[PDB]
Length: 196
Length: 94
Length: 21
Image: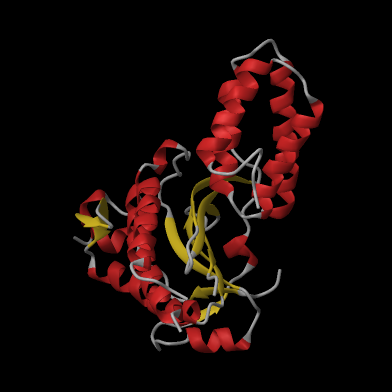
């Protein structure tokens, strides 16, 4: 039944990680971010209300699909000014299907390490051309009608199917940051980065 | 299952350590068994480990011990990369 | 290439609308 608590845990995590990525990749100016501590790590978090709302609407809508485990990967895509994908932060997900105490805090211990990898990830990636936008993509496991239904959870925040233009990146080179395993969660974060 | 001889990253290090430093030999069986270990990390969706191993083997093999270890690394990289290209649609890094 | 990829219709706020502070 744990479907919902892992979804809980992951959503709290992806919010942290998304914010940090927008900061570290400089998709938004230093100045709307405020220093915070999460999983006991120094992080940044926008306090621009609409950006925050945006990121939240997204995670709120994904949540139920995590609960039933239909999401295969969640990907944050940085786009150049021509709307061509420059790089993607790929969170590949598994939820293996029971429990003896403090499992959750061990899981957050492991996620902390992802947050760090993100915060020192300029060391391994080439910087983007300026005027980059970003977007979120949710790759479902199954191509399923049911998926569209459970994702349409806020009117005023619809989802559509992606185009080839949203996903095609020519010649990707791969930069893994972090992998983890546990009884409840298996996840890896790698970056797919455009070649030139 | 995973293992070169066996398993945890920092034990796979010690084994690669004792191998590349002391040996200085082309045990071709053995290069092969490293390719298999690497491509299995691919299939186990364990890319962080795939990268630490590939990067660590670059450090220890590129420095030298003649050059046998220089073609070896090249050879391992080649096969890892063709497999990555088919299973992730991506080549690795450095 | 298939359609198991979902996307929000709405765009995140532009760099400009932020600098609107």
